[PDB]
Image (spheres, coloured by chain):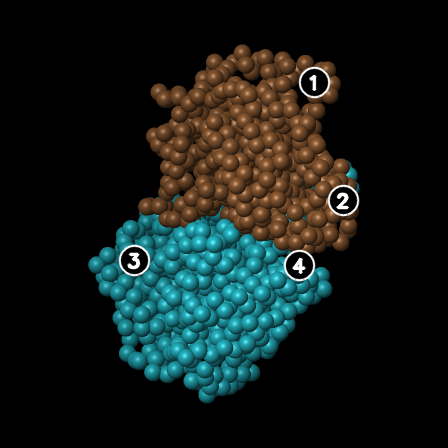
Chain colours: A cyan, B brown
C-alpha cells in the first residue's frame, strides 16, 4: 500500500461551535450565490447552450438556487465523441496514476465539503447532518474506489500454467459509458457511479437528476480542478427523457450505470438488451431501483432502541431513500409497545426549511409532493391513518411525518415505493409470519430486525431476502466499504457499491498465450 | 486444500496399441446401442414422452444413433417446478458437499471416457482426437469448477470493519436457470455450462442441441449415477424453438446460460432484458456467440510452424468451432511463403467417416451442409477459390477443406461466421494493416499471430481486440484453467469459462450487519 488504509470520512453532527460557525458561513455563501449559471462540461471545457434548466429551493420554491445549460442530442453526440477519444489513452494510464487522480479529487472535495453540504441543504432540502452524510459518502466512494482499483491491476487473474507457454490474463476497461444519477444522493451516488468506472479506465457521460443539477455541476468543478483529461468525465444535465434515452439507446454507448425508480430502470434494462443499428457489443446495464423496505420488531426487542431506529429509518431525509423503512412489521407482542413509542417519537419531529436544520425538510419537488399526497389519499382507503397525512403550511413542499396502521400486506401503500415520509405498520402473529410479510413484495433492498432472540436473527440472516440486512440498528446509511450496498429482485442487479466487486462490472478479461 | 491441485486431463493421441484397441471396443459398444431410446430427465427421474427425436450419424445419415424423448411446454414447466423445489435445499448444502458431488461426477465421467468419445465420433462426426479433447475438457470443467467454487465459500468478501458491529458479506446462488447448449462441444460445453451454476448452489434446466441429444443423455446418466438430488439438474431435449423460447421468456427463469449462434444469442439477450408478466427480478443472461477469428502471419514468422497451426485451427473438427481460424491475414512478405505451405498441407488432409479417424469428418447435419455450401457459392463471387469448395462422394456430409484468396476484408465470407471448413485469405501491406483488418469485424473471440518480432507481439497484445489471443500456436483448444475463455464485442458477454470469474456470474451478495 502506498496510501493510508481506507477509513470512512466522519459525518459532522454540528454539535461544536466551530462546526456550526463553519456551516453558517457555508450556507450564507451558497445562499449569496443563488442564481449562478453552470454550463455543460464536455471534452474538458464548459459548454453553454441556448436553453436553460432551473433548479429551485424546495424549502422556498420561488427561490432559484441556480440554472444550468440543457443538453440535447447534439450535445450527447459530442459527449460520446469526446469520451471515446479520451478512452483511447485513458485506458492505458498506469492504475496508480488514475488512482492518484481520484485521490486528488477526494482531497479537493474534502476541502469544499461545507460548501457542498450547504448546496445540498438548499437544492434538495437535506437537513445539516443528512447533507454531511451525503458528502462524506461521496468522499468515501472516491477514496475507496481509488484503492480498490489497484486490486485489478496486472497481475490479478489466477491461471493454471502450461508447459512451454506464457499465459497472461488481465482486465481491460470497457469504453465510454453513461451514468444516470438520482436526486436523493446527488453528491454521493452521482460521484460513486462516475468514479468507479473511471477509476479502472472507462470514460463516462453523466446525466444528473433534474432536481440536483447545481450540486452536480459543483462536483464537476472538482473533477475539472483535479485534472481529469478532456473527455474522461462529461456533464450533461437535461430535461425529461430526451438525452437520457438517446444515450441509453445509442449504438456507441458501451454500458449504462443507473440509480433511480423501478419504472425507469425497467426501461433501461430492456433497452440495454437490444442491439441498436450498427452496435457491435452486448451492452452492460447496472441498475439500482429502490425498495419497499421493512423493519421487523418482535416482543424480545429493546422497544426504545427499536422505535428510535424506526423513526430514523423512516423519516431521515423525509423518507426519500431507497433504503428507507417504509414498512414496520410488528409481531402481536411487540405491536402496542413499539407503535406507541414510534408515534410518540414521530409526533415530535420538526418540519421546516432545511437551512434551519429541522428533523425533516421539504420533499424535493412539486411533483414529488403530488405523488406522496396521492399515496396518502390511497392509504386512507387501505389502512388507518394515525399520524400526519397532511401538507403543512408554507411555500416549501412540507409534508408531516405520516403513519398508517393495520395495513394489509398487499395494500398499495404496503407494496409500492412512495419515497416520502409515509410509514405503513403491519401487524402479524409471530416472527415466521413477519418474515413471510417482509419477503412478499417485488423488492429486496434493505431490511431490519429488532430482536434479542439469537435464533430469530439467525433465521432472518437466512430467510429475510434483502441485499442489506441490519440487526438492532437503522436500515439506512450503508457505509462505503463496510456494507456492500445493493439488492435483490426488483431492487436491481445487485451491483454492490462500495465493494471490491463493483469495479469488476466495468472490466472485461483478455487472455494472451505465447508458445515459445 | 482437500484434493490434489487441478491439472488438465490428458488428451489421448491413440499412439499406443492399447489406446487403439480400447477405442475400437468403445466404438463397438456404442454402435451396438444405436437402437437405444433416452427419455427426458426431470426431478430425478427419466420421463418419457409420446413424441420422439431422432439423432443421425453425420458420416452415414441413414443410420440412426439413438432416439430421445421430446420436451414441450408442459415438460419445461414441470422442470422449472422441480428445479425451484430442489433449489430450496440445494442452496444450503455446504460447498464442500456440492463440490464432492461434482468430483464424483468427474470420476464417473473419466471411467466412461472412451464410451463418450465414441459417442461423439458417431453422433457429431468428431475424429478420435477431437472426441478425446472434448471429453477431456468436460472432465476439466467439472474438476475445475468443483475447486473454484470453494473460493466463494464464507468468508470470501473483504469488508471494512465498523466499531461495535459485526459485518458479514457472503454470496448466495441465484435460483433455477436454463442452459442452452451447442452441438459442437456437446460433452464439454454442455457439461461446463450446467456444472458451473450447479456447483455454487443453483439448479439447472438444460436443453441440449438437437444434433447431440444422445451424448447429452449419456452425460445425464453420469449426473444421475453421481447422485445429484432430484431437480438439481434437468434434461430437456427438444425440436426447434419451442422449449428454449418458453424457458428464456418465463417469468420464473432466474438466469440463462447460452452458447451458440449470434442470431439466437441476440434474441436471448433481448428477451432476458424484458420483464415477463409477474416476473420479480432482473434476469441475467450469459451468451457466448461465435467469432470470425483471424491468424495474422508476418514475414518474420516460422512459416512452417505457422502453416501447421493455421491448418489445425481452420480445419480441426471441420472448422465447426467458435474459435476456428476462418481468416488468414498475411503481410506482403509472408503471403506467398505461407499461402504455399498452407495449400500444400491442406490439400493432403483426409476427409471421410469420422470413425476412421480422418483429418476431417463430415459436417454435422444436412442443414449445416446447406449453409456451408451456400457460403462457398457466395465466396465464389467474392474471392478466388484455390482449394476444395466441393461436396465429396458419400451419403455423409463430407465437404473438402476450402481456401479462398484475394478476399476483400468486408466480403461476406470475411465477415460472417461460416462454421465450416472454409478459410478466407487476405493480403495486407504490413503488420499495422494486419491488425486493422483483424479488428474490423463485429466479433472478438479468438485471434492469433505468428511472428518472431517481439514488438509485433506486444503490439498485438495491446491492439488485437479478442478475448483469447495466441502467439505462435493454434488459436483453438483453450484449456480449462489455463486460458479463461470468452470474447469481446458480438462474440458475447465475456463470461470467461474455465476461470474463477465464471462462477461469480451465478451468485449475488448479501451484507448483514449486527449492532451489539
Query: Can you tell which of label 2 and label 3 is closer to the viewer?
Result: 2
Q: Which mark is residue A393?
A: none
x, y percent for residue B472: 73, 42
Left or right of A144 on screen, residue A348: left
Which residue corresponds to the image point at 77% horizontal and 50% vertical from the top-left? B453
In three-dimensional space, the C-alpha distance between marks 1 and 2, rounded to whole angstroms, equals 36 Å
Q: Using a 10 Å C-alpha cutoff, classify the residue at mark 1 as few (fewer than 14 neighbours), some (14 to 19) or many (20 or more).
A: some
Q: Which residue is mark 2?
A: B301
Left or right of A313 on screen, residue A16: right
Q: Earlier in the sequence, mark 1 or mark 2?
A: 1
Q: Which residue is mark 1?
A: B19
Mark 2 residue element: loop
Q: Which mark is residue A413?
A: 3
- Chain designation of label 1: B
Which residue corresponds to the image point at 28% horizontal and 63% vertical from the top-left? A375
Q: Using a 10 Å C-alpha cutoff, classify the residue at mark 4 as few (fewer than 14 neighbours), some (14 to 19) or many (20 or more).
A: some
Q: Are marks 4 and 3 on the same chain?
A: yes
- Chain designation of label 3: A
In three-dimensional space, the C-alpha distance between marks 1 and 4, rounded to whole angstroms, equals 49 Å
Work out whether residue B459 or residue A446 is closer to the camera in this orientation and state it. Answer: B459
Q: Are marks 2 and 3 on the same chain?
A: no
Q: Which residue is mark 4?
A: A150
In three-dimensional space, the C-alpha distance between marks 3 and 1, rounded to whole angstroms, equals 71 Å
Amino acid at each position: 500500500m502506498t496510501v493510508e488504509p481506507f477509513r470512512n470520512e466522519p459525518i459532522e453532527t454540528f454539535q461544536t461551535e466551530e462546526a456550526r460557525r463553519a456551516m453558517r458561513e457555508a450556507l450564507r455563501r451558497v445562499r449569496e450565490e443563488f442564481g449562478r449559471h453552470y454550463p455543460l462540461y464536455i471534452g474538458g471545457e464548459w459548454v453553454d447552450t441556448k436553453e436553460r434548466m432551473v433548479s429551485l429551493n424546495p424549502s422556498a420554491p420561488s427561490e432559484v438556487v441556480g440554472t444550468t445549460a440543457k443538453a440535447g442530442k447534439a450535445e450527447a453526440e459530442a459527449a460520446l465523441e469526446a469520451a471515446w477519444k479520451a478512452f483511447k489513452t485513458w485506458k492505458d494510464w498506469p492504475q496508480e496514476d488514475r488512482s492518484a487522480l481520484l485521490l486528488k479529487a477526494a482531497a479537493l472535495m474534502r476541502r469544499r465539503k461545507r460548501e457542498l453540504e450547504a448546496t445540498l441543504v438548499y437544492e434538495v432540502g437535506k437537513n445539516w447532518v443528512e447533507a454531511s452524510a451525503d458528502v462524506a459518502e461521496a468522499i468515501d466512494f472516491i477514496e475507496y474506489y481509488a484503492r480498490a482499483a489497484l486490486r485489478y491491476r496486472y497481475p490479478a487473474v489466477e491461471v493454471v500454467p502450461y508447459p512451454g507457454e506464457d499465459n497472461e490474463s488481465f482486465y481491460v476497461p470497457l469504453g465510454a459509458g453513461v451514468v444516470i444519477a438520482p436526486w436523493n444522493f446527488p453528491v454521493a451516488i452521482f460521484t460513486g457511479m462516475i468514479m468507479g468506472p473511471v477509476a479502472v479506465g472507462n470514460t463516462v457521460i453523466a446525466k444528473p437528476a433534474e432536481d440536483a443539477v447545481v450540486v452536480g455541476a459543483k462536483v464537476f468543478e472538482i473533477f475539472h480542478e483535479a485534472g481529469f483529461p478532456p473527455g474522461v468525465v462529461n456533464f450533461l444535465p437535461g430535461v425529461g427523457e430526451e438525452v437520457g434515452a438517446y444515450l441509453v439507446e445509442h449504438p456507441r454507448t458501451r454500458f449504462i450505470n443507473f440509480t433511480g425508480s423501478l419504472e425507469v430502470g425497467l426501461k433501461i434494462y430492456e433497452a440495454a438488451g437490444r442491439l441498436a443499428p450498427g452496435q457491435t457489443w452486448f451492452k452492460r446495464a447496472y441498475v439500482e431501483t429502490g425498495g419497499k423496505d421493512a423493519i421487523i420488531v418482535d416482543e424480545t426487542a429493546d422497544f426504545d432502541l427499536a422505535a428510535e431506529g424506526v423513526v430514523v429509518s423512516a423519516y431521515g431525509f423525509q423518507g426519500q431513500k431507497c433504503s428507507a423503512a417504509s414498512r414496520l412489521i410488528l409481531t402481536q407482542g411487540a405491536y402496542e409497545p413499539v407503535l406507541e413509542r414510534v408515534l410518540k417519537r414521530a409526533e415530535r419531529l420538526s418540519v421546516g426549511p432545511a437551512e434551519e436544520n429541522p428533523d425533516l425538510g421539504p420533499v424535493v419537488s412539486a411533483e414529488q409532493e403530488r405523488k406522496v399526497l396521492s399515496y396518502i389519499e390511497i392509504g386512507k382507503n387501505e389502512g388507518q391513518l394515525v399520524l400526519g397525512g397532511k401538507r403543512l403550511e408554507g411555500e416549501g413542499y412540507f409534508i408531516a411525518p405520516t403513519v398508517f396502521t393495520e395495513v394489509p400486506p398487499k395494500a398499495r401503500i404496503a407494496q409500492e415505493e412512495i419515497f416520502g415520509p409515509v410509514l405503513s405498520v403491519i401487524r402479524v402473529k409471530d416472527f415466521a409470519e413477519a418474515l413471510e410479510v417482509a419477503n412478499d413484495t417485488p423488492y429486496g433492498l434493505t431490511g431490519g430486525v429488532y430482536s434479542r432472540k439469537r435464533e430469530h436473527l439467525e433465521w432472518a440472516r437466512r430467510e429475510f431476502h434483502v441485499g442489506n440486512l441490519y440487526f438492532n440498528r437503522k436500515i439506512t446509511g450503508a457505509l462505503v466499504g463496510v456494507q456492500p450496498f445493493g439488492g435483490f429482485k426488483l431492487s436491481g442487479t445487485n451491483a454492490k457499491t462500495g465493494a471490491l466487486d463493483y469495479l469488476r462490472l466495468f472490466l472485461e478479461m483478455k487472455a494472451v498465450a505465447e508458445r515459445f
